[PDB]
Image (cartoon, rainbow, N blue to C red; front, side):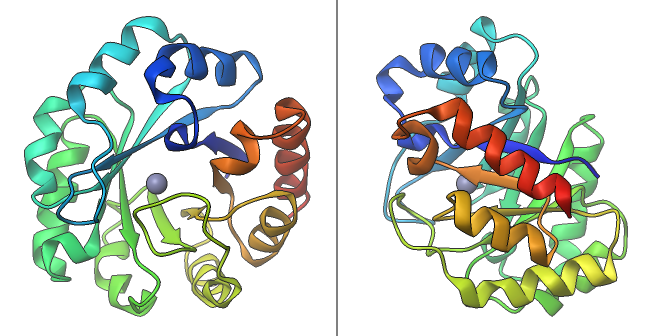
Length: 221
Ligand SMILES: [Zn+2]
């Protein structure tokens, strides 16, 4: 397990996506978190494969972490072959294990990391059957109602994080929604090792300071 900081571009000046990502890259961010929303799974439309595929032309080593907050996530796999991890929602596939296992198999067969996400009201234990197959590289625990940035961190989601870390020691646990210096420390104390932060990084007075502070706090655990 590694301490990973993944700035969420949704909170940046997206009309300058390439510039913002290169900046995060120059500051040492290991991953770049790309939120794809289709105005159906969530009430917001962000950007899709055409934008992400073009961005890849201007980046270097930064890992492409795509969070698919969309219906029919299976349709996006062939459109994002140059990315690094594709994370789909357990809820997008009607919470049925077999369908999730099949999509995960396909994503892994495209030589991509596979992530699965659950919203605040979804019970973490429902993921066990899928997680036991070892096909999932990352579980993205939403710490806020997905769709928009700027919302407040839900401390009551930490139980999900502890459950996962205790049961799966090598599983990457990602938190997303309201992460800042203080809530990153809280998340890491429960087992999170990948931190998605939007507002706290892109609106920071000293971006690198925030990123480094966050990483060290995760590494401590
Ligand atoms: Zn996300």
